[PDB]
Image (cartoon, rainbow over all chains, first blue to last red):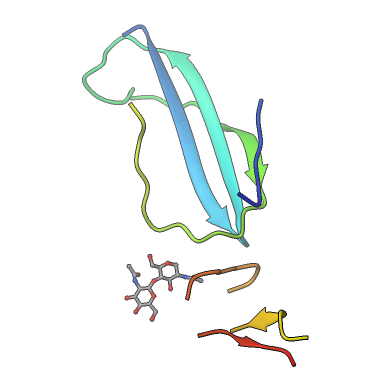
Length: 64
Length: 22
Ligand SMILES: *[C@@H]1O[C@H](CO)[C@@H](O[C@@H]2O[C@H](CO)[C@@H](O)[C@H](O)[C@H]2NC(C)=O)[C@H](O)[C@H]1NC(C)=O
């Protein structure tokens, strides 16, 4: 518990990476026409958060 | 005292066998 923090027509996109023990998150939100596959076109992802965790990561799970 | 225990860049662990400074 040595660190803690608090703050279909559409698609939410994200990127997660860990470097130097800093864990970094980026995002984009957009409307979409079709659900079957990712959109055949370009849009950029922008940063949200930088976390000083130092912890090691090799697996993950999504929460429904 | 003997409480000050010891065994990547900014990598850390607390799982177990540790030494400690006399
Ligand atoms: C981060 O965690 C992984 C385990 O999920 C560590 O990888 C293991 O490292 C040992 C080193 O002797 C290997 O024998 C295993 O085969 C590795 N397992 C896997 C799944 O890769 C990794 O070393 C850890 N890194 C740090 C810096 O703590």
